[PDB]
Length: 261
Ligand SMILES: Cc1nc(Nc2ncc(C(=O)Nc3c(C)cccc3Cl)s2)cc(N2CCN(CCO)CC2)n1
Image (tube, rainbow, N blue to C red; front, top):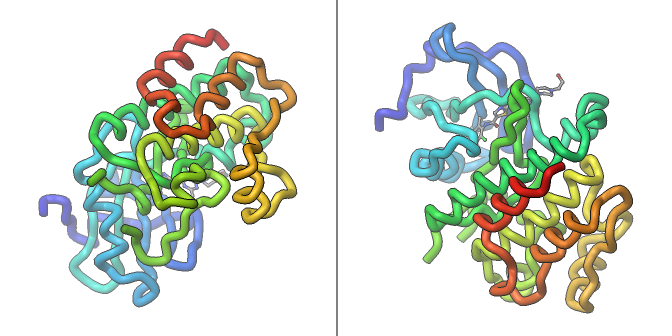
């Protein structure tokens, strides 16, 4: 479309990450605008499936979601160009010495910002399916934005090399293949655990299979050290066995915007 831009109007400067399917760079569109560039490593992924993410981002545009700016899809090395988030992923940020100094009022603010982005996705009739701290990005001004739309779908299917985050996925989605906005709410509850514990892995020392088995037996993570009851009740609401009895993202954004600290 008019999402295509000439290659020359993009200068790649600093390599930020390397995956099996390519690379992530910080760069510049036309000298002016600071951007992030995702590079497709040829042949590993299809070019079709690599761009599936961008095509979805074309239609998914909100303040609390990382914005697409453009693509380069005319010759071999395929680029996806987006809004740049200075602080990197929320997970990595929480584990850093800086994030480890970020107190509970601001942590609850983080989660509310994410609940807002998810309220949009809900309202837009989409699902994310890959909602975790690793897939949220932090700006200089400490704004949290939902990233990584590889597994995202419109309601009523998986991209190449995909892989669901077992420990973040609702049991009904694992066992019955039932991905809905309500399975994202489960994920959000796990994301809340990640925020309050400063980027700790879900179910410490437990294997994915132990997790799957334990959940079918009615296990939920016990209240975490230094996490107020009111916050744990919100997590608990997200992990309700019966999907239909889990809250809306509109409710979560409201209640978290409403928790004073
Ligand atoms: C992995 C990473 N990304 C950063 N910024 C990004 N902004 C937006 C990103 C993104 O991927 N967008 C995107 C694209 C491009 C395509 C499809 C979909 C999407 Cl959502 S990646 C910063 C960062 N840093 C390294 C560690 N730091 C501490 C030590 O200095 C700070 C900075 N590392």
